[PDB]
Image: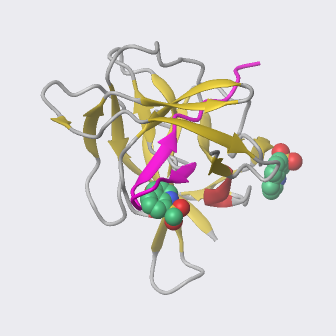
Amino acid sequence: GETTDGVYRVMTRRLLGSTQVGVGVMQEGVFHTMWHVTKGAALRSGEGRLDPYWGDVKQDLVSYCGPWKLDAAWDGLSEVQLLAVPPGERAKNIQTLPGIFKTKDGDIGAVALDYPAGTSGSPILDKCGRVIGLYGNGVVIKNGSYVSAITQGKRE
Amino acid sequence: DMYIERAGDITWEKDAEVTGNSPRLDVALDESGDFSLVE
Ligand SMILES: CS(=O)(=O)c1cccc2cccnc12
Ligand SMILES: CS(=O)(=O)c1cccc2cccnc12
């Protein structure tokens, strides 16, 4: 399979034609995506197979071939970039200053950007190109627009 | 049956389109991993 580091589209042939259900990140031999994209199903990569290794529905994350590797964090002050990979469209970087989701368990960065559902799992990066989280789990605010959490896992 | 296709490198791009606001929202996270607004 293609093991090269980078951003990848997650496709399915179960529905009409080939549909893009999400996006993920390959890093240090592990594929990182959101749980709601694959539900933990096995993934095909050329002639090779990717099997889930860790997953958690509450964090909405899943890693394949190994443990979660992404551990960078938003510094709470700087602008970031969403490396959006929309269905049938080329990868595009979009710069934004994250907002905040305030919860009873602490604060999490949030990105107010609206993209098709099949863009879920696109990485959010800092100025050093480090993945600080994935786009795709959030809320619809008072006017209909979408706001995503910057969802990051834990490197054990 | 799901499959992956490479879409690009992960790199910061100088002079990318700058957009989106920074809302501060009170949210709740349920056991199913769904976020909701708190008022
Ligand atoms: C393979 S595993 O036990 O690490 C796992 C975890 C969470 C969710 C999963 C969904 C489908 C398959 N497997 C899943
Ligand atoms: C309401 S929804 O969850 O289908 C949705 C809407 C708008 C934008 C979205 C971006 C990513 C994932 N989902 C998105």
Asked whether A88 or B25 is in front, the reply is: B25
Secondary structure predominantly adopted by residues drawn in magenta: loop
- Residue A143, image x and y in percent? 39, 59
**Magenta-highlighted residues:** A137-156
Asked whether A48 or B39 is in front, the reply is: B39
Asked whether A25 or A101 is in front, the reply is: A101
Asked whether B39 or B18 is in front, the reply is: B39
- Residue B28, image x and y in percent? 70, 42
Query: Is A148 within the magenta?
Result: yes
Q: Residue at x 70, y 20 (%)?
A: A155
Above/below status of A32 relative to A27: below
Above/below status of B32 relative to B12: below
Q: Residue at x 59, y 37 (%)?
A: B26
Colouring scheme, one of rainbow, by chain, secondary structure, one colour? secondary structure
Q: Is residue A136 visible?
A: yes
Count the marks: 0
Horizontally, residue A6 falls left or right of residue A48, namely left
Instruction: Looking at this view, name the residue that lies furthest to the front.
Output: B39
Above/below status of A78 relative to A139: above
- Residue A118, image x and y in percent? 46, 62
- Residue A2, image x and y in percent? 50, 45
Instruction: Looking at this view, name the residue that lies furthest to the bottom.
Output: A16
Horizontally, residue A29 falls left or right of residue B32, namely left
Query: Is A149 within the magenta?
Result: yes
Q: Is residue A118 visible?
A: no
When asked about the image quadrant of residue A154, the answer is top right
Q: Residue at x 43, y 54 (%)?
A: A146
Q: Residue at x 12, y 28 (%)?
A: B15
Quadrant in which the C terminus of chain A is drawn: top right
